[PDB]
Image: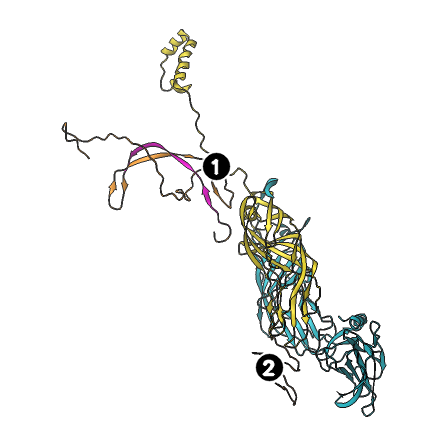
Chain colours: A orange, B yellow, C cyan, D brown
Amino acid sequence: LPVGQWPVLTGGAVSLHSAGVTLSTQFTDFVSLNSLRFRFRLAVEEPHFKLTRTRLDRLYGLPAADPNNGKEYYEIAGRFSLISLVPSNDDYQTPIA
Amino acid sequence: ANEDIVISKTSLWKEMQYNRDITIRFKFANTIIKSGGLGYKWSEISFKPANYQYTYTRDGEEVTAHTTCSVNGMNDFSFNGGYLPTDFVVSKFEVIKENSYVYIDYWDDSQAFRNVVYVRSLAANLNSVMCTGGSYNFSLPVGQWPVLTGGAVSLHSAGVTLSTQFTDFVSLNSLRFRFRLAVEEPHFKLTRTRLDRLYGLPAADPNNGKEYYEIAGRFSLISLVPSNDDYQTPIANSVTVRQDLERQLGELREEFNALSQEIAMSQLIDLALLPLDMFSMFSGI
Amino acid sequence: WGPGEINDSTTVGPLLDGPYQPTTFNPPVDYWMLLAPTTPGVIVEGTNNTDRWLATILIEPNVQSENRTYTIFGIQEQLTVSNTSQDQWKFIDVVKTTANGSIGQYGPLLSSPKLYAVMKHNEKLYTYEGQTPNATTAHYSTTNYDSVNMTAFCDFYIIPRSEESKCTEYINNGLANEDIVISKTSLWKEMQYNRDITIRFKFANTIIKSGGLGYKWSEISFKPANYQYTYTRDGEEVTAHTTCSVNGMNDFSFNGGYLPTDFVVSKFEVIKENSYVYIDYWDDSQAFRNVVYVRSLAANLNSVMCTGGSYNFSLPVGQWPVLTGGAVSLHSAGVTLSTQFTDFVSLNSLRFRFRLAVEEPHF
Amino acid sequence: WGPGEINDSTTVGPLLDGPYQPTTFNPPVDYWMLLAPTTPGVIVEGTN
């Protein structure tokens, strides 16, 4: 703000829980990747987000101001299970791709 | 004239009085400016706008406050022990007296303080404090240095005056708390000059080397603050409501089996003959 | 609405027009000339060139009759100097009937603090005579009193006639942490206005003169000036109440001589580029009733071509100096809408600030 | 939230060395004694 007190968008938490998984295709500047898309449903939590020096107080959700909150990354650890079909014409020679 | 237009729709405001303990630390300053000549004369020995910054433990949380102090309404006396260049002619010694009021501007970074805009009323339960005058030597190319001795003055709280300078579309705030000055013992003597036992803090040394003039007092500020109450939010603004746990399936099955008592054979046969379909089965559920 | 609390530049007037060094300067009618020495010798010589050659002369305490030669009125002659007091200095008046004839002495004057006063009234010179604290104001009858040239050899002061008591005194002994809700939520609305209003104002001056002749101008600053007028703004008679002041102006001092009739000007204020004029208007109209909780404010006041004052410095005798020149324009410098909450009532003061730009001619 | 103005006035021609009256004194270092004479006669007599 050029003059006066600086408004601040502080707060706002959400929780991510798994809600299925499906195939997708990421891309890079040189190659395309056969990625897996994990879809997570959201759930707002106790930390509220306010807009100081205003009248928007006690709002819930995660705004887009600084969703990372200074963290380098958010981590979700778990397990996935897939059964892929491989074209094997013999009792052996199971292809590895 | 004959014109006026609407800017915005109506808004929700409320009146609220903020009561806060304020500590006041303001050190005076002296110009003490030497006029031309051999060095005996003085242009205008007067108080200057003295600025400082502090941090106080108010309400259990540190508050950072800028502090400007000045005085207006002082009496300006003159001295003439001879107009000769080797003699002592002082144009104006500024002295605080009953005609003098101290004006002090405060800038605290606290919440209510920032909220003090478009205010309704202010009450200041400040404490009167004694301010004494020190001594200083007036430079002279020849002769002993003249000095000050004694004196004191007392500050008494008076009306607070808040101002807002309007530039373009910005309001620059300017608070000014006022203190009436009442002179008190001891008295002021200037060496090698006429004044003997004069009263009133001079423009030479009102600080007296004091750390700061600590005045502790409460302040009640009734101002029209803006607020929407707990409204103007989304109709579903709250933490996610956890769905209630359903039931233990074992006991659910137990109760379902127990329901077999309330079954009539003939009516059950009729219901069995009726072909339940995707509609009939779930219509009344 | 109405109040104004900007008042600075206090002044003190020299009670006796300050000290004066040895020279030929006389006391005008209704003005005592007081004399304060440093060391003995000659004090004053009042010469009419016609019939009066008075001379007030110092003598130390405990001094007997001694014959000494003095260069009085350019001629060396022998005179007798004597004292009667043992602790009080003597101020003896030598009287010369004629230049050729002998010269006498009278007017023994016993006072410790070394202060003594002379005057001219009612066909008589009023010279302090006698012993302290009863030192009288004895009188000598002669002609052409106002023409007496008073050539003196000490420090001096000038007093009014009404302060004979002061002259006698001088001769006899010398000089918490919580918040609460007041009222529930209410309805408000920022409201715009497009209105033009005429503005007119006057000035005033603190003309503080020194005590005595008047050739010593202690100070001339600006006064807080209050006025009232009526204006027709779009068919609505408004009683505008006006209060003026000025701050941050540049000042001058002048000295044509450090002596009584010499034109001395200790301090004079003058509006200049650095100067700003604080101007308060009060109107009972709806706009100025609604201007309490104001969000924004902008004034488009046009320039004001201002010509400086021109009056003749009042002095008791002699040519009158005058001031002419130095025009000034005024430009908007913002508006301060201050509120002053005393213990019970709120004095709401609106002050437009006007920067003063300076322009020819030259003062 | 910045401080407001304070009523003040600048110095009143302080650096004006006026008509120092004629008598016996000792000129100090770095003070040129400009003169204002009017009629024929002696102006200054500096005696060591």
* Quarter holding residue B97: bottom right
Q: Is residue A2 left or right of residue B162?
A: left
Residues in magenta, as a range: A5-24
Foreground mark, 2 or 1, reads: 2
Task: Residue under label 2, please give it.
Answer: D33
Seen from the viewer's position, the closer of residues B12 and B17 is B17
User: Residue C338 at x, y = what percent?
Assistant: 62, 54
Dominant secondary structure (helix, strand or loop) of the stretch shown in magenta: strand
Type of the residue with mark 1? Pro
**Label 1 neighbourhood size at 10 Å, few (<14), some (14-19), many (20+)?**
few
Seen from the viewer's position, the closer of residues B103 and C298 is B103
User: Residue B29 at x, y = what percent?
Assistant: 59, 61
Report in which chain the residue with disc 2 lies: D
* Vertical comparison of B69 with C135: above or below: above
Disc 1 on helix, strand or loop? loop
Task: Residue under label 1, please give it.
Answer: B234
Q: Is residue C128 left or right of residue C37?
A: right
The answer to whether any part of residue A77 appears in the image is yes
Q: Is residue B182 left or right of residue C146?
A: left
Residue at the extreme bottom: C100
Type of the residue with mark 2? Met
Disc 2 on helix, strand or loop? loop
Seen from the viewer's position, the closer of residues C183 and B115 is B115
* Quarter holding residue C110: bottom right
User: Residue C285 at x, y = what percent?
Assistant: 65, 53
Query: Does the magenta portion include A20?
Result: yes
Report in which chain the residue with disc 1 lies: B
**Label 2 neighbourhood size at 10 Å, few (<14), some (14-19), many (20+)?**
few
